[PDB]
Image (cartoon, coloured by chain):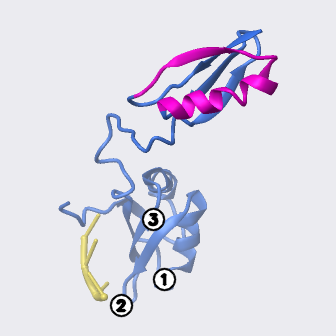
Chain colours: A blue, B yellow
Amino acid sequence: MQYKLILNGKTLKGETTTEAVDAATAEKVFKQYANDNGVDGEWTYDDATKTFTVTEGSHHHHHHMHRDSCPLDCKVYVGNLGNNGNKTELERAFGYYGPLRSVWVARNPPGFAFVEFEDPRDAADAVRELDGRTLCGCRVRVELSNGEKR
RNA sequence: CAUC
């Protein structure tokens, strides 16, 4: 019986078919043809239209409509926290919403500090649920850090 | 939004 395959990639994309028994032969035929175009992403199958797919993430190229919202932008600010310069509380508070990359706190009876996350969405979620309330024992103004010029 |  014949089966289909789609090679959804950034630049090289396409589709083909083959005579097989089922996935037990189609899943060891398309593996060659896909690598001959050069795709080798998410190996998929549809059990109602009998059509494989391989949505690319292996030919080492991708871009879309993003720039000033990347892993570089993840720096954050926190202040009016309460008298604490030990980082541990705010560090687990930050990394709780999602993994950090760096944390800083000052030297003179502080209640003010700085932070950097790994995903800019970890910083965004943290900023959205750490602000204007309380964390250590104060009112926590929490913002993205303005401390850059590219 | 710096006390590094």
Please state if A121 lies on the left or on the right of A27 as rendered: left
Residue type highlighted by circle 2 = Asn
Instruction: Give the answer, above or below, for where A57 lies relative to A128.
Output: above
Q: On the image, numbered disc 1 is attached to which residue?
A: A84
Spatial CA distance of label 1 from label 2 is 10 Å
Q: Which of B4 and B2 is in front in this view?
A: B4
Q: Which of A45 and A115 is in front in this view?
A: A45
State the residue at coordinates (35%, 38%).
A63
Q: Mark 2 lies on which chain?
A: A
| Magenta-drawn segment | A12-37
Percent from the top left, x then y, of residue A65? Answer: 32, 34
Looking at the rendered structure, the secondary structure element under dot 1 is loop
Q: Which chain carries label 1?
A: A
Percent from the top left, x then y, of residue A139? Answer: 45, 65
Looking at the rendered structure, the secondary structure element under dot 3 is loop
Q: On the image, numbered disc 2 is attached to which residue?
A: A108
State the residue at coordinates (46%, 41%).
A59
Spatial CA distance of label 1 from label 3 is 13 Å
Location of the C terminus of chain A by quadrant is: bottom left
The label nearer to you, 1 versus 3, is 1
Nearer-N-terminus badge (3/2): 2
Q: How crowded is mark 2: few (under 14 residues within 10 Å), some or many (20 or more)?
A: few
Q: On the image, numbered disc 3 is attached to which residue?
A: A139
Q: Nearer the viewer, residue A121 or A90?
A: A121
Residue type highlighted by circle 3 = Arg
Nearer-N-terminus badge (1/2): 1
